Amino acid sequence: QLPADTKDAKPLLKEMKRGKEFHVIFDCSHEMAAGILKQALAMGMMTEYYHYIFTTLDLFALDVEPYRYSGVNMTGFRILNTENTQVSSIIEKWSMERLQA
Amino acid sequence: QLPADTKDAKPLLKEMKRGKEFHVIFDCSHEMAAGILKQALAMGMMTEYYH
Image 1 (cartoon, each protein chain N blue to C red):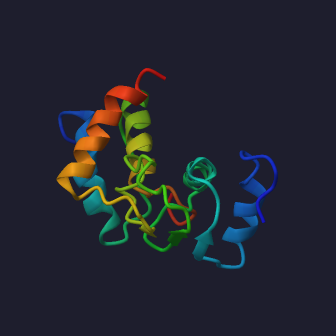
Image 2 (cartoon, chains in turn yellow, blue):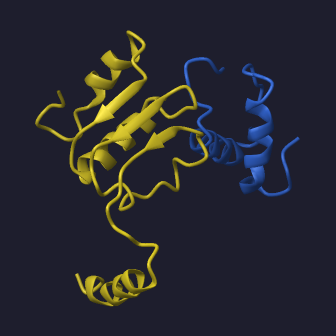
């Protein structure tokens, strides 16, 4: 179980690196998911010798630019049918409407 | 040998992690060393195995 603080995942990942736990299901929001991926990158969990599965439906909202060269096997679920031209054009309409915030 | 640009160290490090070469002696300036360390963190080379 993660602590109440988002940034205090270092003792949990330290205790998880010992004992050889690699195949990890994560169940949180995508903000806590991005924070725990940053915490996993900060102490050497990002390698081809690990695995990650996220139960969130917002895995595509993360930025995997500093992670995709490490060769991790990360897998998630998406319900947003972005392959359609109509839905992607709607999302392109929302891109002009979300950048005001 | 590193390439002429510091940012082109990704294929060199991709060839480095193949063949399991872990004990690496880097000879450069400290700015190039910082670029090497940043791109090695991005390439997943910074584990407990390496030196």
